[PDB]
Amino acid sequence: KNHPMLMNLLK
Amino acid sequence: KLSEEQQHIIAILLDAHHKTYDPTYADFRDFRPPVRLSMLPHLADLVSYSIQKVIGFAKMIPGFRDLTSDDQIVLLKSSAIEVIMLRSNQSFTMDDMSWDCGSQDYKYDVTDVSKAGHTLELIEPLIKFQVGLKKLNLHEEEHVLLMAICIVSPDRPGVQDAKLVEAIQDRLSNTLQTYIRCRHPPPGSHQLYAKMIQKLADLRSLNEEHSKQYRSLSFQPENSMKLTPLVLEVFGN
Ligand SMILES: *C(/C=C/C)=C\C(=O)[C@@H](C)[C@H]1CC[C@H]2/C(=C/C=C3C[C@@H](O)C(=C)[C@H](O)C3)CCC[C@]12C
């Protein structure tokens, strides 16, 4: 929730 | 006996770490140049870089993918500074009580850490931690396992599926316990697992102090401009 960059790197 | 699955987990972790940790530190040049809050631009960049490397390591951990992305996010946000402090041990040198990255410019000392927004309250306990962890003289296999166990922690606040997160952690912890017994020779072995777990407790406290110090630094808008957006998203939340 409001973690755009961290979510993208996690993918 | 050490099992085939457990041997597999160690091989995976060691390789994931080699991929995410460069002992050359070649990328350091990409960072804003350090100044000797003179350090803050340079050190914020190193942490931002370190966060990315930690994430790349975390993805490799067996059973980490099974977790919901949200659970992946919560673990990484809470463990990031702790893993970065654990990983740093590799650069940390007892000789000068400083992190050595290969060059004088990239060699970091308490004054340098102080130079970029951190009190001794954090720094004095952190240096004690690096000394105590260094004394353990861990096998690389042990060091990699500890980082993984630290990332996958059931108790972190916000965790949705602790049952799964504990089951993944338990496999890693059993692998570490079995590895110390089978491949770690006394005396070093003595109380080695319990001491490693104690280091995790030291991390929690170091993490908490970091949160309060980062927040104080964060509150000033000008200081906040110095940081990277990825640092703001994770430690800033
Ligand atoms: C805290 C600021 C909050 C606003 C800043 C800070 O500099 C604190 C967080 C510490 C944490 C760990 C420290 C260091 C780590 C060094 C390395 C070097 C290599 O081993 C490596 C690639 C690791 O990832 C980390 C030393 C400097 C201060 C530091 C960033």
Image: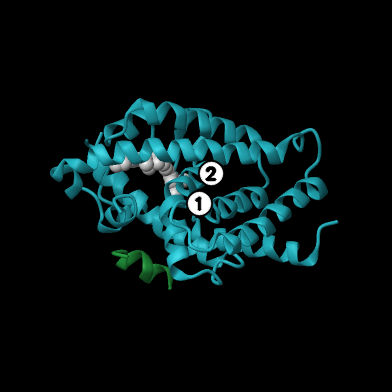
Chain colours: A green, B cyan
Callout 1: few (<14), some (14-19), or many (20+) C-alpha neighbours within 10 Å?
Answer: few
Splitting the image into 4 quarters, where does residue B185 fall?
Answer: top right
Residue B105 in sight here: no
Relative placement, left or right, of B39 versus B141 is: left
How many callouts does the rendering have?
A: 2
Going from N to C along the chain, the mark reached first, 2 or 1, is 1
Callout 2: few (<14), some (14-19), or many (20+) C-alpha neighbours within 10 Å?
Answer: some
Mark 2 sits on what residue?
A: B90
Mark 1 sits on what residue?
A: B23
User: Within the displayed image, which quadrant is ligand 1 positioned in?
Assistant: top left
Q: Nearer the viewer, mark 2 or mark 1?
A: 2
Q: Quadrant of the C terminus of chain B?
A: bottom left
Q: Residue at x 56, y 41 (%)?
A: B200
Q: Chain of mark 2?
A: B
Element assignment for label 1: loop
Is there one chain holding both mark 2 and mark 1? yes
The CA distance from mark 2 to mark 1 is: 8 Å
- Image coords of residue A2 (percent x, y): 28, 64
Q: Amino acid at mark 1?
A: Pro
- Image coords of residue B121 (percent x, y): 37, 26
Q: Amino acid at mark 2?
A: Gln
Relative placement, left or right, of B153 versus B217 is: right
B177 vs B19, nearest the viewer = B177
Relative placement, left or right, of B141 versus B210 is: right
- Any atom of ligand 1 within 8 Å of the CB at mark 2? yes
